[PDB]
Image 1: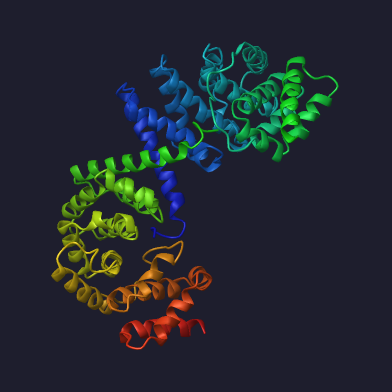
Image 2 (image 1 turned 60 degrees about the horizontal axis):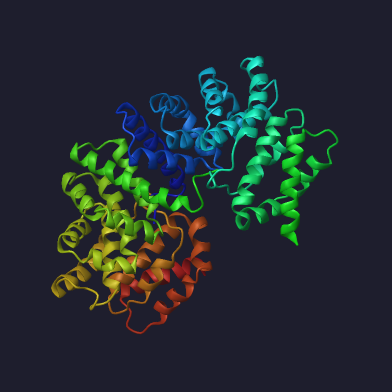
Amino acid sequence: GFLHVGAQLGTELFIVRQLLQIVKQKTNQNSVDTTLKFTLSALWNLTDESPTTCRHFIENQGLELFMRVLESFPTESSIQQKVLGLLNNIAEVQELHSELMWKDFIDHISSLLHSVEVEVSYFAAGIIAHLISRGEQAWTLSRSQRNSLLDDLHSAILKWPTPECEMVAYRSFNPFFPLLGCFTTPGVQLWAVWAMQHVCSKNPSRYCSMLIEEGGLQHLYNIKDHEHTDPHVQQIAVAILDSLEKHIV
Amino acid sequence: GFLHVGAQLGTELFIVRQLLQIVKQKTNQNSVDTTLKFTLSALWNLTDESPTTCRHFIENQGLELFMRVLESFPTESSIQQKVLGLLNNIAEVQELHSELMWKDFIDHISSLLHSVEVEVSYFAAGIIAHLISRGEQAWTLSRSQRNSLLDDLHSAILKWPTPECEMVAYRSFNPFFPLLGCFTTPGVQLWAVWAMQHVCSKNPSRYCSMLIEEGGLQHLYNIKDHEHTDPHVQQIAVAILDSLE
């Protein structure tokens, strides 16, 4: 039994508030411990495909707190990964895009894009890819920074080695599909196809069938068949398609 | 995206541990505040039909903490209801029965059965009903206490007024069905039919179709036609049936 009809949502939101309170306490104490790491993991996990949780995070000063986490722990790669992983989930929510148009936030993300650790850079890239995908008018910060970020995003992806593990898990590829259509901003497409390639090659039994079942073949074929595709985007799309085509047969 | 495949279970259990830490802190501070009330609500909600969450609660000293809560806040009805609501969920898990065969725990439940507030007594009665339903050999405490609890359970239910609103929500009636067959312990059946009548009369659009779809009618018919049925069990069972037929 439980408190009342509908009470589970109120409990979910309370849990988010209390996890942010732990983050705040650990950050105040400059204490990187197991509790903080499990707390950042939990918030990342709870924001997965959950606009309701993403919104509640924003409304409880989560963005400011998480910038404080990055400033307080600049040498903690695993902390940065979990912070950025959550923020990548926020960045997928179009209704929250305006909440991320904050110079202190974008400047932190832009700098972490240049981390040599792929486990950090990858999520900074995902945030930027989603934000840039929404178009120049949706971008209410400096136009010059948006244009620079476009090039930095493209160049950063091309430097990444093959990571040792899956850096992330996905329940669905649906959030990536709008990115695959962004022909006028190739770095956005490049992040999406690199991401799909990474998880499909690491874990094809989980992800290849999922990608096909959700309609990924048509989206990838539309990139391949597009006349004037960025050469790096085209190459990863073709590489993914070859794997997928062998998977169906 | 999320941490790694299968990570949500580890997050769920961590959340339980951290909610228990909050209960411990508020009890240490003697602070009946909104955060404590939401934390107890959260734990109640998280143990709903969740044997794995109930076990984790037990393994992180939840039972002793909740006894301490009951001792620290002896006249806080809202706190007592939320503590007992969670414990009612534990009492539903057969595999955890022996963890509740603890004299100090049962003495607390027995005391709350005698609350003048039905919103507290109801959940103490639920714990007792589930624990008694498991039979005499599973009851490893005093046989004398089992027999008095069975009497006290029956008489408590007969005193309850109609509550002002639904005291609890359920996702399923399935945990009540084993209680409906306990003809040799009528107080256990009485709690189960009283509880069914309560939610069906307060919220028929949610609960009447649920009862029907899950096979509740056959259990009530079983009671209606059984030879030497306790009259109060019989009356409510017939009232529920007649409300549907």
